[PDB]
Image (spheres, rainbow, N blue to C red):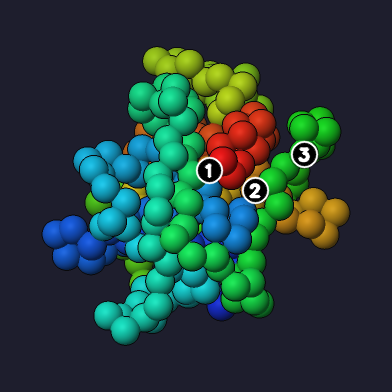
Amino acid sequence: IVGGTASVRGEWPWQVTLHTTSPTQRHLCGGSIIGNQWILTAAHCFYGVESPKILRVYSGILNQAEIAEDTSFFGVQEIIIHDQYKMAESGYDIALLKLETTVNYADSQRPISLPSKGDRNVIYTDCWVTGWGYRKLRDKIQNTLQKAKIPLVTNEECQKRYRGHKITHKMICAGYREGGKDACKGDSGGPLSCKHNEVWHLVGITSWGEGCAQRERPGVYTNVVEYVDWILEKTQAV
């Protein structure tokens, strides 16, 4: 996260840090708890990932330093990538991680509500992007979970900033005309959470952007509300 500040422990209880154990353990991407056995994240986070066996999901974390070899984690039983996903910039950058065990909810780890189709008309004015991503294009994974308040921008306005791309209604952007605050490498898969009527909703999933926090370059996120049907269908037992 560029231009953000340290989060308060437990402030974003749905935020998880997804690690890969190959070659050695390290933070890979962010993600959000949306169900007792489900993490919603970005599909592009699994590039080069052949098996769920090398993944570890850690919940209730503020500082990466809290994670040691003796720290408990959730194994991943299955990685579900949207069948239409090709690459972040083309959309459909969404994936589900089915955990091997269920998360026991507590003040430090609980699910975030998904947006309702009836809220697509609602204008969010209190949105935050969080993560352990870079603090600057050329940086490294941060120890403390960072947060930054960023205003949503209309898709028409976003399209104007990315003339070489197609900003679809399945995407949502957030940023300052002057830049300065934005997600960055390592924040991918994490949430764009907006508080509306005292209730937090998972509005977007950190996906991509031209560099990080640049002027006239809003961050691009997966528009979660456009995938509630997909999420329901994929998270059904059988």
Would you name the residue on which mark 2 appears? 202
**Which residue is at a point 72% across and 42% down the rendered structure image?**
115
Q: Which residue is mark 1?
A: 205
> Which part of the image, by quadrant, shows the C terminus?
top right
Q: Give the amino acid type for the residue marked by disc 3 in the picture.
A: Ser
Residue sitting at the far front: 238
Residue in the image at 40% along x and 54% along y: 77
**Residue nearer the viewer, 107 or 139:** 107
Q: Quadrant of the N terminus?
A: bottom left
**What type is the residue that disc 1 sits on?**
Ile
Q: Left or right of 231: which side holds 1?
A: left
Q: Secondary structure at mark 3?
A: loop
Say which amino acid is labelled 2: Leu
Determine which residue is flagged by label 3: 116
Which residue is found at the position 44% from the left and 60% from the top?
Answer: 100
Q: Is residue 71 visible?
A: yes
Whichever of labels 2 and 3 marks the residue nearer the N terminus, that label is: 3
Identify the residue at horizontal 48%, vertical 74% (top origin).
Answer: 62
- Position of 149 compared to 120: left or right? left
Element on which disc 1 rests:
strand
Task: Determine whether 71 is above or below 44 in the image.
Answer: below
Instruction: Please say if the residues under marks 2 and 1 sit with CB atoms less than 8 Å apart.
Output: yes
| Percent coordinates x, y for residue 179 in the rendering | 49, 43
**What distance separates the C-alpha of mark 2 from that of mark 3?**
10 Å
Quadrant assignment, res 119: top right
